[PDB]
Image (spheres, coloured by chain):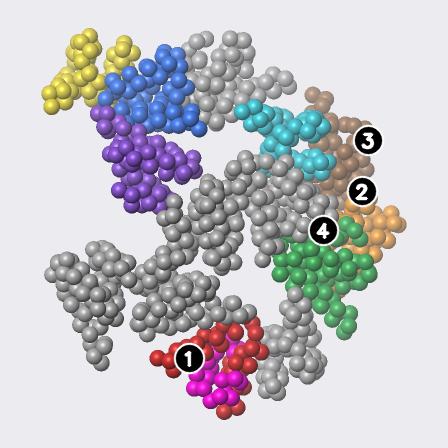
Chain colours: D green, E orange, F brown, G cyan, J red, K purple, L blue, N yellow
């Protein structure tokens, strides 16, 4: 549907911004998602936690504790 | 008994909501259990921690830090 | 949704009542589900059939023959 | 041929309704087939009996004893 | 021996009608054998039971339960 | 011992009648044993069930269901 | 407690009567348990089903079908 | 759901018509699905493409080129 | 047989009371058996001795040395 | 980079619409991309070609032949 | 030494309360130890940390973060 | 449970006193448990007999010989 | 690229200060980077997190928690 | 420690008197230790029990049963 599409797009954009090596942009993305209460945020965090990147795990944990 | 029955039902519901991919619902469930002081909460947490899902571990830790 | 949730809860409760070693309670559960025409009944029966317990298969067949 | 075509379509519809996890619909399909005396019914039963699903075998056996 | 001949012929006819994929005619054969009291009915029944076909075993049990 | 002797004789007669390939007479034997209320009947059933013949198991179950 | 004691004693008595080779006495035991409504009836059936004896399975199923 | 049901039915009918060895009827079915704008058409084409049949691949490609 | 019946029941009751982890009740059982001069006492002592439990061997020896 | 971001987003959306099993939506997306001359179209096509799904290759070729 | 005695008893009580599946009791025990400044607290915490239990890890960390 | 707690505490205290190499304190513990009639006395003995220490077996047997 | 050059130089300086065994200066470097809002900070953190040093991980997490 | 020193010396003297092949002297030593209530007695008893030589085990048991 549209919810699943938004989830997938947010996860893909997080993965992309991570692949460029610009984690400040990943943080900004996650903060924007969180401030709006978009459930897609969780999808985003999933993409990071499955990435196997320690910086990704740190960013995910920080943003999640910001809840 | 009824206590063990509810301890099993809460864990099953948490595992279910995790299977659908709805961690916001898992958070809401755990928050309700915590605000009600239901000991079954801990059972729920167990169901998450052995689930082998990083987001599940994050949710468990974040809701534990509120005890 | 709510229907998959009720199905999962009924299956888990049947599994729990069987694990306690109270097949009379499993029979009571199944008869209550059947008398209401709740589709979740089938979700229950599956749980018993795959459990690998001969008494579970017996209870499943005996309650299914009442449809 | 129309006979073999209807046999194949009934078998496929039974397999589909079983794959969705809706055994009530499979039961309704089989009862509708049986009440009309459509020989395709037996094809349907075939599709269930070889499916390797305990609930499928139970439904097939329950439909036999009404013949 | 005419008795053994009729037994063999009934077994072969049941096997054949099963091979065409016409279990309704197999049922009709078994029903007429049963209504005639022909002992050959048993020669057929084990044939089906040795075919290794679930539909065959089901038909055999369903017609045997009518004795 | 007359009891064990009659048990052994009934079991052997059932095995023999099954070996000739005359399941109708096996049924007649079992029906007579049942109508006479002879415990030897169960011995006769044993010889049938541990024999390994599908028709034997069918006969055993059909006779046992009459108790 | 006393309920576990009832369960264990009934299961052991059923196993003993089955070991003596007196399935008529097993049937009488199970019939009495069933007519008295003792939940121990199920503990007995377990003993019979996990025993790995075909006649035990037949007695278990035949008694269970009377519930 | 009716949509997935029609998808499965069209795919199964295409598979069947191909199994009879009647590619003209497969072409006629695909042409009907295409002229009706039924999305199930794609569910049909997939069934052919994974069929491992070169004639199935040719029919699928020739029909798809008409979009 | 009533004698083997009581022997099996006493052995099973001792096994049960030992399985709960309640050896004081095992001691009470063995004491009441001994003071009654019930030969079933030796059926119990055997069940404990083959139990492979050091506490069982000690209880058996302590009771036996009172003969 | 915004160009690279749009490329990645189009590729991800095509992959998603393909994962749902909705190739009509994939065609709609590809035609929308093509009608505007968005270079991101090619990033989409690559996404489909390395997917391995034969329907994906067919869609890619059919939309490429329109350039 | 009474210090080693109290350390061992606190560790054993924590391990036991964990074995019953009552982590609320483990939390209450650790809280009581902490509020009194009993060094035995650490003997308890180690007991949990070596238990190889995720919930035990969480309880240990959450209690230790209160010093 | 309080009684299970006391059993576990007595077993752990006996194990501890054995670990220090103070078999006189183990004897004093067992003697006080015996004189108080505490059923936990057995949980203590069960702890010693399994420890695999000859002096432990001797102490356990000497305590048995006083019941 | 000056941005990439600074990103590389900050990570190299952090690695050098870690190799010298002066984690206080690593902390001071990370703090001065953070206070200016320099994206190079993240390039610094990677170098630590991928360094495989526990003190490096602790420093990385403690600095990241200040964002 | 003088207590541990006396324990070690008593254990060594027992081992010595055993090595000479003079178990009457070992018995006299153990009796002298026991008559004074010296805890070092147990240090001797262990030294014998682990040293094989079933004569040593018998002496240990005989002197222990006098406590």
> Where is residue F34 drawn, in percent x and y?
79, 32
Q: Residues within 10 Å of mark 4 (few under 14, many from 20)?
A: some
Which quarter of the rendering shows the C terminus of chain E?
A: top right
> Where is residue E34 drawn, in percent x and y?
85, 49
The residue indicated by pointer 4 is D61
Question: What residue span does the magenta drawing correspond to?
Answer: J31-56
Using the rendered view, name the quadrant where residue K8 is placed.
top left
Is J64 in front, or is G24? J64
Q: Is residue D46 above or below residue N36?
A: below
What residue is drawn where x is 38% and y is 82%? J3
Question: Disc 2 and disc 4: Cα gap in Å?
Answer: 26 Å
Question: Disc 1 and disc 3: Cα gap in Å?
Answer: 86 Å
Q: Residues within 10 Å of mark 3 (few under 14, many from 20)?
A: few
Dot 2 falls on which chain?
F
Which residue, as the protein is rendered here, is positioned at the far right?
E36
Left/right placement of residue E39 relative to residue E55 reads right
């Amino acid at each position: 549907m549209e919810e699943e599409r938004r989830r997938h797009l947010a996860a893909a954009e997080a993965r992309f911004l991570l692949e460029l090596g610009r984690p400040d942009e990943v943080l900004r993305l996650l903060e924007r998602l969180l401030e709006e209460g978009d459930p897609a945020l969780f999808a985003a965090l999933r993409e990071l936690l499955e990435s196997g990147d320690p910086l990704a795990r740190l960013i995910a944990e920080t943003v999640f504790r910001r809840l």
